[PDB]
Amino acid sequence: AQYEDGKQYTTLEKPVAGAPQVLEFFSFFCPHCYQFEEVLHISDNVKKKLPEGVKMTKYHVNFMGGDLGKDLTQAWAVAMALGVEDKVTVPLFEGVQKTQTIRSASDIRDVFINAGIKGEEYDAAWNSFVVKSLVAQQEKAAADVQLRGVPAMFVNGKYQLNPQGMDTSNMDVFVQQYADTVKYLSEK
Image (cartoon, rainbow, N blue to C red):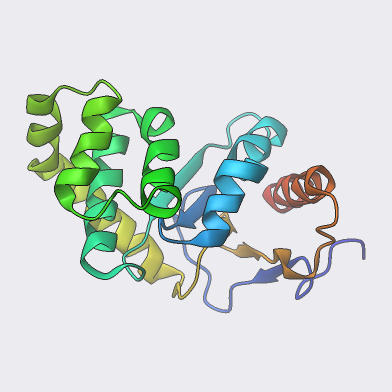
């Protein structure tokens, strides 16, 4: 087959029922995640190829970066709750990995303040039970698929993308193969 179980994707030994249709995991500490999001723009290109009625979810993980990693999972919950993912993703990646100016929870907050979220609104969201539930959802989704690395993408709780054997000499061709594979998996 052109797409083969065990090659371009793997089928989860213990499928996860009720999972999101397309589920990404990342860490703002993760160098390949920086490439995936900042240089390759994987999520955007996957979205552009996906059928009607297939929605995408992206969650942060705790297992990189210790205390600040867990602070970033809560900040990502704030971003989701406020709908400001597209305003804070680049400055959070750059703050952690490029300028290395994000060293504390206050530095994370500064990114949201600079992006135009009012301080009282950020603080209310940060401390809210709506955000606690989003943090729990991110942790549960990672636990469901027994996640030990990022970046990772899962389709319909059944299939995991396997980019490692793909040709990466051309960034655009790689992204297109990745997106076309997600599309194929979504149609199974």
